Image (cartoon, rainbow, N blue to C red; front, side, top):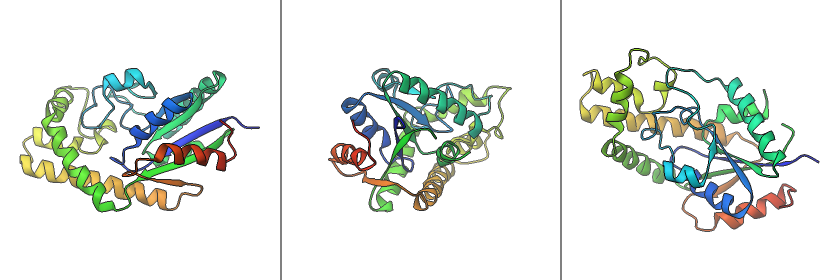
Length: 236
């Protein structure tokens, strides 16, 4: 009998963290982030990282574990995730892996001693996701995204070509700081870059087997998720 585990994936801005919290309040879970961008300290606003207050009540493994000058491979995630899952399992907690970096989920599934329930969440209409992505990006700029990147831009040990600055939107803000883009162009292109990410994420998910979809606009995803666990033959 393999211990339980839950995968909660979906495109950027789908509202994965909201369902993760509901699950964490219903079952003894151990939240594990599966995101190549959230691992970086100092990159919180532009990455839509959960607030410090939220993280305090809902701790996430693999968030703020690297400095932006460092790299992080899918192989490293694989090792870190397996260790986090084992530690959680040893304590009777159900590993709940939430995120949108599909390559990471892939590395874990391929190159898992767990019975896994795989859930995916996204709005029925992609148009709804795109509208939220644009608005969310514009709000990031209002909440300090530029000053955030300004601190990174000022570091001599960082440059626009690093893996960390690959986080969607960051390069556009960086180029703006270099005087190469107007505020409007930076905004449009950061939004485009984020829609592009969602498009790529949907591509990975469309060919993903054993996925149970959830609607981002539904108010009863918690009960539906719990029922699926039983479907996958996971008791409690």
